[PDB]
Image (cartoon, rainbow over all chains, first blue to last red; front, side, top):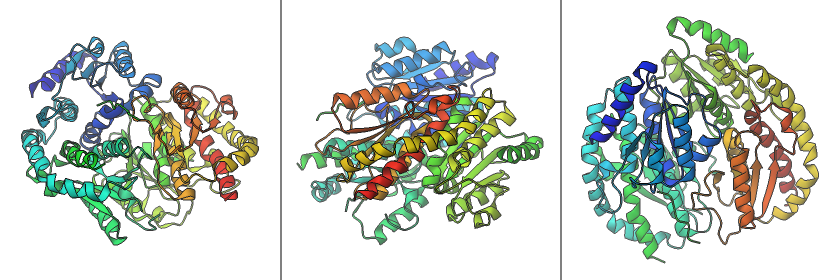
Length: 313
Length: 308
């Protein structure tokens, strides 16, 4: 909704006399780091005069970019608003004169004292996807772009935000039966690989981790689809995220390659889960929200079918 | 010279609005070889953008900034990788000058680029001129010849020292690598740990342990991401190959190393500080971790293949 739009115009206004916004930095740890992958992929694809950088909090605070200053905006995210590195990150940005936006569920958290602006997001079961953390990240990018250089697909993006909640809740319904089978076939497999490309790749990275948290044997690789174009194919099975949008052809090629070597593949296809009502101008950017919110159906069924590391959302 | 190549590009593009975007595009080994170039531009540049792309992702979803104000650096060892050739074609179609990096000067790749730079390869190679260092030199020249780079001479000092550093280092670790090869011949997986500009070296060493061991392709673990659990500490008792870097991310590495010791894990520590990297000035030392680690691992990996 209207929070991000207003935050960003505040920033645009405030920095206009100092040469404007030229750099965006997404800084987080844990699951928040993966969840900003769509925003980076957006600005890399769509911007001509905005740099984007995606940083682990620890990297950021020990090795801040030279361009960190009054022409930069820093978006940080911490679920509980208590992540020391992320807090320092916000601190270091303010010391350099960069406006900071914080994403948190907790408005009273220590993080809030170190951000010029705070945006919150929906969370938990039956959340409205349109306002989820990943979507606020992306909306920061789309507004920063819209309000500095213009974004030709702004309306199509809002259309997409208006459709994604219903798409996602219907899709969780649609995969319940299949989720059952899935957990039958895979409950004994010790390791599983995930495969993805494009703006949704972060969601497959997180799925890799949910798996390791379940198996507790070896942290799986998350493999980029583009590694399955050519032989040689260098019995672990594959959880395949089949994207909609401009990297669908990369994924299709990879799936065909995996089929040819007779591998075991669980395919989750955005095209078959209702994502295709979102226009092709912007659909790239909604794979994450889809996959990230459908993989729980599969994970719960995997857990029902047979070291406690508390993850950072 | 990468210097003359970049000079020629800055010349040709000045009328078109100049160079504002750098794209590194490759697959596999080549992709991770460009990680330091990415880290360098992200750290040091104020005007230039930098993007590191898998070839198949680049040709299927090219950025709208691909254009007359972009320079594309592709790399293909043999110069035949179709996706990498396609990437060069797509860039040329958009008016982006292309620099090709290849070992084979006639290869097909050369025909699809505006400029071709080669690098040293194989046993007995000069590290100053290897693939990663040519990647980095493209970035240092692109920065220096558009915006100015404050530490250009310190970097060139660095380049003049790195070869001797690596050769000495590889002789220095030879004994310990023998030992190590005993203790580790019976583990189908070992993890790698790293951070900062030389993280690509750890990614490549993960591929090389998958190459040698072949059981499971295991995570390359960004040092930062242990205190944001889960942490890869389970019954499997997977050992750790630890890259202890010098420069701005040494502190992140040290904190990761301490963590693993608290879980009494089995850790082979390769420390840049004990391998002589510190003659390079601290202003540029971050960018030479990769060339050190990428070239010391073979000593260990060769002695693993030995005791097997």
